[PDB]
Image (cartoon, rainbow, N blue to C red):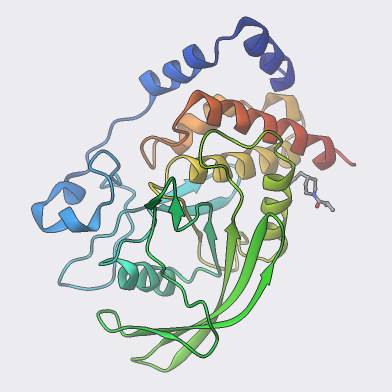
Length: 284
Ligand SMILES: CC(C)C(=O)N1CCC(Cc2ccccc2)CC1
């Protein structure tokens, strides 16, 4: 059923909470035993948000391979994403180890470091060119190369150096800075513009490792970003765009990480973004 008509029928009937609860009830349940080991308690931001064992990203080291991060692999769309929590004071070195080992080109950040007067993630990148960061636990160096500040987002060029081999790579940091402290944006126009900028960079393309996407827990805003991207790509690839079922795509992505899309308002915003996005992917 054309999703724009499904949209107006849920709005007129006011049934967003009922649709959202049906997704919660049908969602996959897989074990997360590595996440719950006592040695990993200070590697998790939230006790109720864990990566499944089958899809978790492993760090390349014998001591402790654990990070709160999942590989979302979308077979028909031919896109992969890593979804992760905002880094903690003791996991900033793990975070950059993962970017290095997975060959990622881009990091997508959808939160501010402080929101609602509390810290939502560590200051994990350098703010000044001449003040680089060294992560001694994982043997990496990170330098700010340039910064472009726009009204709705900031793009940064970073240099990551593996101090063991003296190899360097360029990482692009895409920082969406205007998601409101409460609720969802009124219009999806700036979020879609932002997604279009990440795509244009090459960060989502198969010649690179998967993009790393985070917010505070790495399930809500992060879920909205990957769901909108995958839905718009499937509308481009298929003979009948109207066959793309956003609820079925979200349940497929929930096989790989729990809890993606945290509220009925986030679900409605995802529909809104895909609908308005479709009006240009179909030729405009
Ligand atoms: C100049 C033009 C090409 C442009 O900037 N956009 C972005 C916003 C909109 C929807 C959209 C579609 C796919 C991925 C992200 C956003 C239409 C295309």
